[PDB]
Image (tube, rainbow, N blue to C red):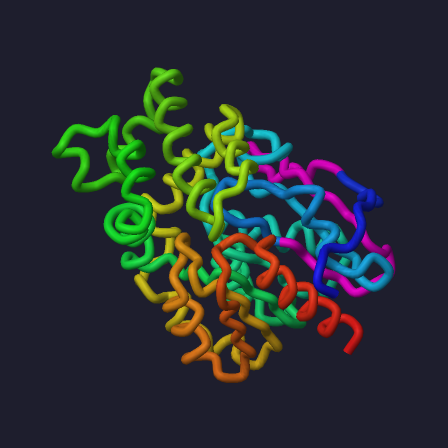
Amino acid sequence: LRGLYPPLAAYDSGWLDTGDGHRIYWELSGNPNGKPAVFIHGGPGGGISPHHRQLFDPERYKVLLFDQRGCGRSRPHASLDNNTTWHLVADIERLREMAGVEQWLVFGGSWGSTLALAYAQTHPERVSEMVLRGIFTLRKQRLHWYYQDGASRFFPEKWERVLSILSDDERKDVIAAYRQRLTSADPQVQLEAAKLWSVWEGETVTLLPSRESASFGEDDFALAFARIENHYFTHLGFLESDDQLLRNVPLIRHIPAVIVHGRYDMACQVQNAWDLAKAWPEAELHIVEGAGHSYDEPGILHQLMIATDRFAGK
């Protein structure tokens, strides 16, 4: 189809205690005995949404949605204690064993494409196919484009607000100036910065401006989102190799995949989708023209709904 499936209820939900201070939220909607699928939300620190359920066929898919760690209803709110790429990879497996799935489709866009890759490349037997979107491999060039010099040139008026709170010395490294504030003993300080990191993204993640970019300002979300995002970026996704994710594709090349990406996606450039495709020829790349970063862009949504329907009713 072109649009989302109609709204529906999760058939199950709960909290999985990780054992190191974390209790992660997880839903279960679709079909009990259907094709097992997992949704991997993006923007490190963003959270799942009821809309993420309407993205898969109700009668054919059993989708597992889960809040990441310190975000969403996942308990330890804004907790950056034991919250890295590799810890999250462990949570996907727990949820798998728990869910009782031996292998499933990994649906994840933006940061979720990152985690999808990082998970697929360490558990190649647990993914049947992958549907990636707005590819994000976490290379230094990519963090620099959205948080230092690049996206800035397209939203000069929006980036001045993000810079307003930084001293000139502090302006030569936005990511770090923001890690100070975000990890301030003072929380009013860390909320002022959190609201400025969040809104920047919510405002450049769509081609045309939408009113729903306001949600990124909301204190709680903005506190978790900003500090979790800046956390992972500060550690470079916790990968030791700028290109560990590209330079590790052979391990999953054998896995059916579809790659959707907006030509004008300002959060993660097309260059990432192309680079990954240039390395994974068996994957079907779809550079949707006239669109931005958000999954819900009409052109990106289409290809996503098409990939999903195909990967299930093959």
> Is 144 placed left or right of 169 in the picture?
right
Tell me which residue sits at (67%, 70%) in the image: 307
> Is 277 placed left or right of 313 in the picture?
left
Considering only vertical position in the picture, is 21 above or below 122? above
Q: Is residue 22 magenta?
A: yes
Labels in figure, total = 0
Tell me which residue sits at (74%, 44%) in the image: 27
| Front-lying residue, 280 or 237 | 280
Q: Is residue 280 magenta?
A: no
Tell me which residue sits at (69%, 46%) in the image: 51
| Front-lying residue, 300 or 61 | 300
What range is drawn magenta here? 14-39
Question: What secondary structure prevails in the magenta region?
Answer: strand
User: Which of the image's four quarters has the C terminus?
Assistant: bottom right
Q: Quadrant of residue 136?
A: bottom left
Residue 22 seen = yes
> Is 3 placed left or right of 143 in the picture?
right
Q: Quadrant of residue 263?
A: bottom left
Location of residue 2 in the rendering, given as x and y in whole percent from the top left corner: 71, 63
Location of residue 12 in the rendering, given as x and y in whole percent from the top left corner: 81, 43
Considering only vertical position in the picture, is 310 above or below 182? below
User: Which of the image's four quarters has the N terminus?
Assistant: bottom right
Considering only vertical position in the picture, is 233 above or below 81? below
